[PDB]
Amino acid sequence: GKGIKKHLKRVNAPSHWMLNKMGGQYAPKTSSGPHKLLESIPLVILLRNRLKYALTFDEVKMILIQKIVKVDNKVRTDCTFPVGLMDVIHITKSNEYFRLLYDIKGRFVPHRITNEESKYKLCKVKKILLRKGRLSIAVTHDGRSIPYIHPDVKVNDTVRLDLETGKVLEHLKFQVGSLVMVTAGHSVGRVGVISSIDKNMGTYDIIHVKDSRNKVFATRLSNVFVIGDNTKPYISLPREKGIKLDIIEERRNRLKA
Amino acid sequence: PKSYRNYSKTARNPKRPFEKERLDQELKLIGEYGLKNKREIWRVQYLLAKIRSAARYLLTLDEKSSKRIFQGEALLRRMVRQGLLGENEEKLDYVLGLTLPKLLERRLQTKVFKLGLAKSVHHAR
Amino acid sequence: RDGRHKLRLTGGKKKIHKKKRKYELGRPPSNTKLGSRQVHVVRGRGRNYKYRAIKLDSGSFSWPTFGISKNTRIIDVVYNASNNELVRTKTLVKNCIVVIDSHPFTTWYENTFGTTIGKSKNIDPLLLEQFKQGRVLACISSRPGQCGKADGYIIEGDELLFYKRKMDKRN
RNA sequence: UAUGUUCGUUA
RNA sequence: AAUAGAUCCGUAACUUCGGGAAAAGGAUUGGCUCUGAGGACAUUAAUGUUAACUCAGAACUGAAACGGACAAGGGGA
RNA sequence: CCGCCCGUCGCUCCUACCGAUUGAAAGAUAUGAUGAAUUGUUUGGACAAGAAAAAUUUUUUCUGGAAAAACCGUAAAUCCUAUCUUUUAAAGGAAGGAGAAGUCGUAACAAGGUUUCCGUAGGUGAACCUGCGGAAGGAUCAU
RNA sequence: AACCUGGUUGAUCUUGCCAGUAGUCAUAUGCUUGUCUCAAAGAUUAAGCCAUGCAAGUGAAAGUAUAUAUAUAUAUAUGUAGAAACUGCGAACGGCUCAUUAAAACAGUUAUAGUCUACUUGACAUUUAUAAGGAUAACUACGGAAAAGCUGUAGCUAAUACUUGCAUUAUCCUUUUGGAUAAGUAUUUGUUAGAAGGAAUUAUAACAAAGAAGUAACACGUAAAGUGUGUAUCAAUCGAGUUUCUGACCUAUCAGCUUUUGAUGUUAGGGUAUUGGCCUAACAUGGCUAUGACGGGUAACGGGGAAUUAGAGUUCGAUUCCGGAGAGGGAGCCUGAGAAAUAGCUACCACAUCUAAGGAAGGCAGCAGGCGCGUAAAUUACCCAAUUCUAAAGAAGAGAGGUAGUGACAAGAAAUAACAAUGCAAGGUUUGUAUUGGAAUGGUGGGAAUUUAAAACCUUCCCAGAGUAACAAUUGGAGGGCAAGUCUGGUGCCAGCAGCCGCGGUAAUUCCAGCUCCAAUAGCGUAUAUUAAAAUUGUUGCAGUUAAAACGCUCGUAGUUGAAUUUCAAAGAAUCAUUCUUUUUAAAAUCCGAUUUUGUUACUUUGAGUAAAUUAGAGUGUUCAAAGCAAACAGUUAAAGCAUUGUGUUUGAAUACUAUAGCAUGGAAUAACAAAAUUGAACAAGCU
């Protein structure tokens, strides 16, 4: 037969997972769920390769058995669970709170965050659709369906969801002053103010983004996540602050020590 | 199935196997550095060919090109770390000038014989 | 049972590998006769059920000029644009022309309009002549081998004149 | 401005 | 003795390119009930009256039989 | 030049060719015939449960339904015919090549003793000879 | 490293090949082999045939237990478990192989507004009830058969197996509040209205007909109400099927193919999950082709990639990853979300096993292993410890996978000594050089630490353990090419060597030996193939009077190529003497002296989107190196940082490449095409 494949070879795994060639033949195929396998990491490599809490898959299972870890403040016990582009992880035994972000090299890193910070989730709406009775639902990058969204919300907006109740708090638009984070390209992880939105009829609409240092980079509109307005980002960013530095002069900061 | 770890050859056979003027030079070098085989000098000149090839590629790129003014100092600082270049040598033009003796003077046995410890390079080996 | 074994666009024969897959499938036709209602169940891909109607005698039929639908019974099959063998054997297909009992429609007209929303469409003579005859012409509009029921609509106006001329400069 | 053939093989 | 009519298909070597050739060699054929195609004639784009047997296709039917008798090449190297 | 050298004819071996033998074999397609198994539909109808009565028995009915059969379809497989591809036998015929030293002549290289050579046609033991028309790569760059 | 040399001759210069030369993650084989790391391995021929054994199973709160065993306060209640079996899920993944296959598959690039999608995630539902029905496994008794993962009859019993079946909400208004009104999820048909997309017959809404399936008659327990299982629809996700554009080797001694038998298209339908000649009916005569159709060959799965590369190239890619296809050859089919599945079934063909002769059972191109085949390829080993998958999901399985065995396939590091004194030689009391004679050290054996699933190896530590350090290096050569003997014997045109030129008949530098020397070295030859050499396939970049090679000549279609012409300079700031940057100067539509767009493509520049492995390349002392993707930092026993008493801290895993095709984009040059007169415009006014 030719049903769905259920194995993932290590060298076939996504590169940002950082699975060593010599450390086994297979990679943990993430279970289906909120995020795509390509743009998410499983909990096995979240608690085994990044936090180094576990030394093995069985240890990851031992962690998950005790209902300690929560993803979007609800208990998750699946080892191959997609974490996602941006979302909160709570380790209750060790009290600590993470948000999955991209570093400027496009790799998923758990950003330490505070308990008060760990109630806001930025969800990028992807589809707005009205069902029976003219009720409007927004399907977000996370994969949730939020009904009775505000009519002002558009397709590429972002919403600040309250984790415990799943309700929108405020929405952010996509003006040329709105700061965004890039999601999958060469410039994955950068944060910038949107230079402009070059819209072309029938193909990918391109958007140009200004870094903090006035460096312009363009990207496909699908690879953009509005993170704040022109004042400040609505989330704490990882230590790089979403600024990508030229390889030639990153060496200068590496050498100075 | 197959192992994923790499493996490469570090020496290239010289071709033209009976050049008298090459065999004599290479025997002079072998004896005066006390090394066991000419495969060793082949490894060293294979290395030197690799460094020279990289440098020669860099010189074709114009100055203030990003590739050149990244890999040029990468290679230059690597060379000064190996010690093949001194303070009196500073540019990409001098890595082209490196030679087999100045590559061989960085071997452990030559360095220890020069520092003392052993009274001969063969004793050091 | 689909896709391959044909000639190329140029007329060249294609060497075949890739023996038949199940998803090409290709089930045998339903030759829906006219008679007592019997349907069978076909399990298609994904456990989606398709109702293959072996015989139907009644059906939902719509008066479109008034936009209503009433449940009547099919009396006879009189035309179809495809092979004439289908009408001769009286098989129901998606565009077949059938004779439909007019009494539910005439009774509905009596009850709502009186006498024999956006009402008062003024009707036509060519259709009420059939009504007086008691049996009226209708075109099937559903797919009986797919949904398991024969539904249709009364034909009136130019299309009715067309089909009547086709059925009967003529013999 | 008649005719006049041939020379075994190798080194 | 073997077919042998007709329809559809297929037809080699050789060749004076005309043939060979009905080469060789396959299939079908009744009855019944139908379907389609092929004309002529008059009226103010439109509707009636009327004629040949000729082809093609389909259902059904039978003790699988149908050029049913008659008539009617054996082919090939 | 006691140089070089050509071809027939003889002997041996090797390669390939033509070859009657309606040659042989193995595959592959195409048509035709027969056609297992089976989807679907119809015909069935072992029974297995209901509904009535009589106060262990019976009729009728409703589905559900197993053998088995038929018809369209999917169609393996075998056989006949045809074609093609590959390999291969063969009396005889006729090439080529290779043999250290065969017989016959002397064709070419000198004006090679008839200048050589081309195309074409005929003839002859062989090289070759002759006719017609060309070339100089000629033995003439020239009254 | 962008390289050449021997051979036609009496000698010469050419052409030209032969031979030499080097590499091959390229196979075989000969000889040889002390260490350690590292690791390819029945692809080539036979997708040939297979004995044996294993390779897919699954229950730790959560369907069903009076098989049964046990335990707590007193025949009770809680239990703890649980053989078997029913039910659920998985077995459609993985692993193997490369026969088929030549616009097919595959790759990049689209579409699915033409569809399906289990597990998982988020939303969330409509036309006896203090809880409904029979019937079955397991089990019990009686059996049949030589045999099989065979099963008959009778009797019981459950289940989240199978089947029935029990409130409510929304809207209108006087206007927190009162009355009134209405009730089908998908899907199908008819008539209509109409947040987004690039475009809707979209979402959705109204009316009229049908209408699935469901909305819990189910199980266990967390905060000082929860979970499991099941369920309608939508969405997401893991995917799949189709699909657009572009890209492939040789062959014309394959030139016309396709079209009754669907070939090309229209219309209608059937079928499908959906579009579609996919199939059927009618109709028309189309469709492809010298820009190579249709054929034939491939000792052809495609790609990522490999070898060789100065640059171009040439050759290879069965094989780690991706995609495809197959399970002896075909065909068919059930279950299922998913299979035309093959350690599933049905049949035929070919093989083949048992049989009591009646009948049964089969599919190693899974892991080992056997035969055969061949030049050509390992253990019928150990384990689930890691990686990861299935499960009723910690706890069980897994020949997936890992570990070791065999292993000169390749690859990396690296022993076979080093040192001091006299003799001898060179020389102005310096180097080489056979005697001695003490240090050093592995290889080896034994024990240990450690390693490991266990074991082994590695590493480290302690014992012995080297002088002919017998702990003894080989392979192939010595005429030239080409490094190295006109040394000694033997043979004497023999035997033999010799890639080529050649040597061999008594002086053999070439055979057979000894000595010596040379070369590479734990490696060195040989065969075949392939790359460079080969500018001897030539785009870069060959040759054609005579070396091979200008068609007899001209015309001529395809192809290739194609004259000139349309908008040109000046002024300023900055290195050193110059260069380098900025502005305008026609015309038509926007802005009340000033604000701004002005063919199409090729081409070129930048981007976007690019799986990894491999490659290039940044960083990093695996003792070096091949490597790997890690790691680094103070701590004979604590300061610091920060936390309001403790909490390690600092990092990396970059960049580039990913065609020629496709998307976006700056564009002045160079090229085409468009527009341009036996005539075609624009403006003003009147008229429609």
Image (cartoon, coloured by chain):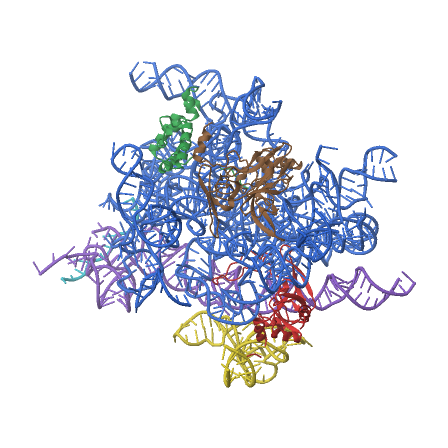
Chain colours: A brown, B green, C red, D cyan, E yellow, F purple, G blue
Residue G251 location, x and y as percent? 41, 58
Q: Tell me if I can see residue B95 in this picture.
A: yes
Q: Is residue G578 left or right of residue B106?
A: left
Which quarter of the rendered picture does the N terminus of chain C lie within?
bottom right
Q: Is residue G320 above or below residue E34?
A: above
Which quarter of the rendered picture does the C terminus of chain C lie within?
bottom right
Q: Is residue F98 above or below residue C67?
A: above
Q: Is residue G107 left or right of residue G92?
A: left
Q: Quadrant of residue G561?
A: bottom left
Q: Tell me if I can see residue A18 in this picture.
A: no
Q: Is residue B94 left or right of residue F30?
A: left
Q: Is residue C136 left or right of residue G581?
A: right
Q: Which is nearer the eye, G99 or C92?
A: C92
Residue E12 location, x and y as percent? 46, 69
Q: Is residue G19 above or below residue G643?
A: below
Q: Quadrant of residue A34?
A: top right
Q: Which is nearer the eye, F47 or C94?
A: C94
Q: How many discs mark residues in the rendered view?
A: 0
Q: Which is nearer the eye, G608 or G250?
A: G608
Identify the residue at image location x=60%, y=48%: A137
Residue C64 location, x and y as percent? 61, 67
Residue G175 location, x and y as percent? 66, 51
Q: Is residue B122 above or below residue A110?
A: above
